[PDB]
Length: 271
Ligand SMILES: [Mg+2]
Ligand SMILES: [Mg+2]
Ligand SMILES: [Mg+2]
Image 1 (cartoon, protein in one colour):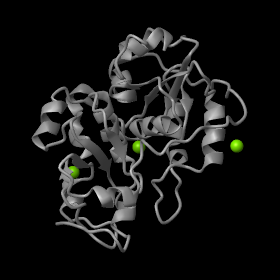
Image 2: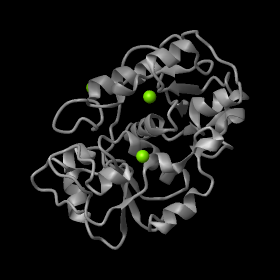
Image 3: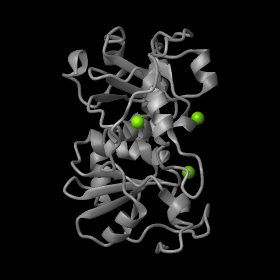
Image 4: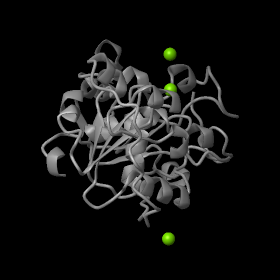
């Protein structure tokens, strides 16, 4: 992991600024076309958040098709020595989802910029309006199912002693007060910790430093397999990332999420 190998998964703006010219760095911005054009971290390559999603029924939060991933990753310059640093401007949902995609393509070396652009801007760090050159054509990817829980896999695990389901939606969605599918409620046995509750707004949307204790209060502990989800596996990108960042050995993103679970005929719902 060359220049980044000594760092933990979640790095600070200072760590990234010192390493902006590292040749192995693939810096990925998942803010927005407007934010990226207004000014991005120097050398950052834009990945519109919509491109991280299949975006088609019945489960739009699934990973994009092979063709789209192969093109995307060739555009970013995916290569053997690459080290990805990922950020967004919303506290890490899209960044964390992109890191789940990095696990899907088997990429081992990557970091999350704590607080993303929010923290970068809060510290008045340099911005660029320049475009890096896309590396090239599509790369042939090896796609992995390990990082992702399927609907059927999750159905078979429900109620297991060794499972925690981290529902990253708002509490109103978790309790079925705010219903965005045929069925309202949550997956049986799941616990709720909204993605934004994991951020610290007083520290530019970095991950709260007391996160471990808060996850432990909900029984989300590293000795359990953690399956996390929201409506489309956007918000649960952050929560997936946090579990990985804390060193939890068994973490899956339930990509279908509530857009699938709340609408599928087979899935039990609990209020
Ligand atoms: Mg946004
Ligand atoms: Mg092929
Ligand atoms: Mg709220």
